[PDB]
Length: 350
Ligand SMILES: C[C@@H](NC(=O)CN1Cc2ccc(-c3nc(NC4CCOCC4)ncc3Cl)cc2C1=O)c1ccccc1
Image (cartoon, rainbow, N blue to C red):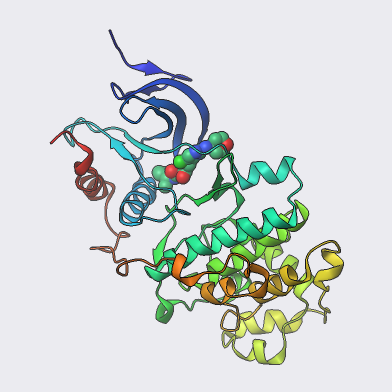
């Protein structure tokens, strides 16, 4: 009648509701498949996560689950269901069921020229999702083309909230060259100078990078290592102004910048000769060196480039700010498992 399905070695212990599995992919998170959902009669994405042997996998798992169960928005991936063992003792895996999406913006950019109309619509949707995220006082912190899912009609949904944080602007400052987790090519210049990435402006930078990559099918700042990232940024933006330098009070960071030879700004219309001029005006405001001067999500949405889409009444916000009950670091592997168990109880037969 039935048994545990396998795919590429792994038990996919998702039944009886989810059958007829096909491999999609794999990564540090675990493994993903499409499955036929027998209750909704659609194929769905299912990712098997096995995080309980290291506490960082447990952190990313719990952030993802707690945030995405709280959020409800058309441009943010939901969680449809969660499968796991009936007891903590028996729970070695978590299967998170999500809407199946045809592709992602990373895959699309490696194969497809984007028309200006596509770029405009994708950007609208990224920002409309990010408006909602930021309205819940949450930062995604790892926005990049592979975290933007697309269906066959180019509807876009933001995924992967494992690095997300509640914003904390009063604790954003750090020293020069502080190590960072999120993806290098989409890191704002301030991460490498004086920022822990605890403000909304870090996501706007990444969106800026994504827009540039939509315009040319190539990453704008493909740094090969921590500090090379900053030098790619300054290679295009040019040397910071005295005003922007004076906002960096950390001497090591300031003096690093002062030690560099003077570079002029490469104008956007030379990097992007076929781009719409309104798109480059918005790009410029998103890829501003000084995070205080960088455009905010709601201002970006109101930019002339997006005028055909802009409608604040149809760009919803969250009902209330997000807050974690407990600080998720300094919490052991063993407690994060318990919290995962609790957070997934609603999907159990009961
Ligand atoms: C926090 C957690 N990380 C993740 O869960 C990150 N992932 C992995 C992943 C894989 C697939 C999809 C996906 N893909 C499609 N279609 C594809 C069809 C083929 O072309 C590409 C798109 N459709 C719906 C979805 Cl949801 C979403 C995610 C996601 O968000 C973690 C990390 C470390 C440790 C522990 C937990």
